[PDB]
Image 1 (cartoon, rainbow over the protein chains, first blue to last red):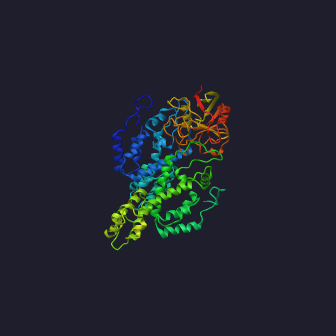
Image 2 (image 1 turned 180 degrees about the horizontal axis):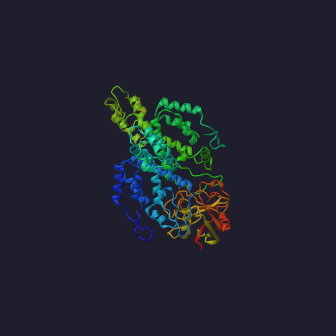
Image 3 (image 1 turned 90 degrees about the vertical axis):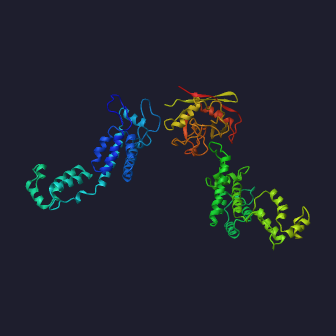
Length: 218
Length: 218
Length: 164
């Protein structure tokens, strides 16, 4: 990682063990719950591609998942290189070589080079952009580890509405839908796949109620 | 091959199918006997590498034998490349390059190039060089299958001296031993492996008899 | 920017004149860099006092064998040979500079200087620079070649380096 507390540009530190024991542990005991994504983000803050690789490789279990995550990275890395022309002659004075799909995944670039582009003005933030590729992977992976699918959720007649919204939310959180749809699902779809006695009370209550009231109906 | 005078006009045409039937036939008929070798030589007059390859490719039998041979040929091809560096820099119009081991093998070259080499002044006989690299592997394949050791040739109790000589000389043929070691063997070992009653007669013609004076007796 | 490099050309001892070259370092960086550093001799070896061993009228003039002197020697500044870097530049006509090699991946220090348009060399020899001044001295050089490449005079890079 990079050290926060230095006012100068780009002073760095060898990766904590505690950071890596906790990553392995949340992967062991949370089983790719969507909760893994903000957690992974607290841990990976301030980190480099060498360090994000060191993190990726450290997980010995789960090797299918790990191969899927790397397939995400390489697809993004192919995209990254497809989009950009990339200059092949000597660089002009005071300036540096612009980073490829391999340089951000940290396979051709070395630690010194990774440091160079974050030093620079504009910085190119290769730890962030590699972490973006890793979060985009894990967002696929969590959905996949989650059995439930949002339209297959429907309230039993005898099922409490607190219990039903809990599982609805859990299923919705894991899904990968556009915002506007999610707004519509939370407005009309949720109430329409409720049970009729419950939906009869929810309609009676009306749409002008608080969500606090809506949870204490039925 | 080259056809109608190797020092003539230098007319060329394909390896005859009449050559090929006689060639497939004789390995079928005669195995890896050393008799297929001058048979190979007399078929291959003025032949290109492309012609020689067709001889090997068409056979369809003997695929371990052929493999062991093609491996032996590639070792001689490799020696040629190793011994000869090519002089660096581009080919002039009207001129032609120095041939490597796989060029004479016919694998990194075409007939147009082979004819060039073969019909330059003075002629560079790449066909001949590669025919010898075949025959050097044939000699080894012959020897592999060869009737049992010469040093173990010993006249039998119901066996004439003529048949013994026969058998002795037939083993001397598929032996690749020096013609000096073979002469000394024809002289010494012949007699000292002969049967007592025959050896006596043989010794009693004295030292340094002609085979005919020996065969006349015994 | 790549600084222009020159060779001084002498023939049999007697000077013949000077050749100047410009190298396409922006297209072809370690090939251009190789012929530039072997021009200075900053690495303790290079083209200075090494004969032109293959000269052929209306095709090319070849040199940079500084070890054997015969067309089987030469070595890159990187040691041994190097990979064909980029084959973008065409052999577009006389004064083109391009890398003599024995088939794939053999570019040492040897090169050849086009005195005709040689279109069949595109994709086999990397074009890595082009003649700046002194092309008619390479016309004077060619006169001392023969059809097989055999030189009938000793043709020698007297001095070489780079230009501000």
